[PDB]
Amino acid sequence: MEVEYVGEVTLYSFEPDPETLFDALLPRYIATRVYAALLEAAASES
Amino acid sequence: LDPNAIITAGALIGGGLIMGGGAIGAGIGDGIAGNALISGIARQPEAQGRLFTPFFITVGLVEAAYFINLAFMALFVFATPGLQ
Image (cartoon, rainbow over all chains, first blue to last red):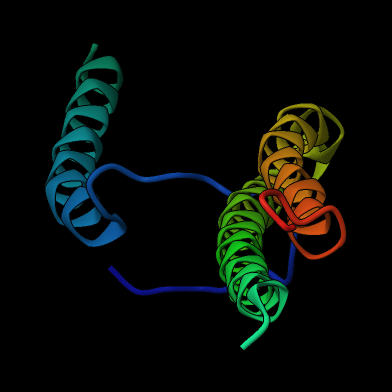
């Protein structure tokens, strides 16, 4: 995944830290995108 | 060697200790409370309004002690107990 920056909009608090949360979340994002693609494919197939 | 001279020197040393302790405690306690307040405001800029209510309390409980010390220091140097 590449990164595109959007210019601009109280910050957030992350437990334990942003790095671990990001590492544990990004694969979940990949799974979410794969699932969305699968559902889209099912709808288009029907 | 006047007794009053020794008593006055002891009173001055005692008042010095009282004020040193009071200043150390007051300064460091105020610094710690201010650290809490600054971090809280940095995280949540709008929370400042509700952060002064506890902060002031803390400051009170600190400054009170310091000011209490002050009173007793004035007691030592001026109304030196036990002075004859």
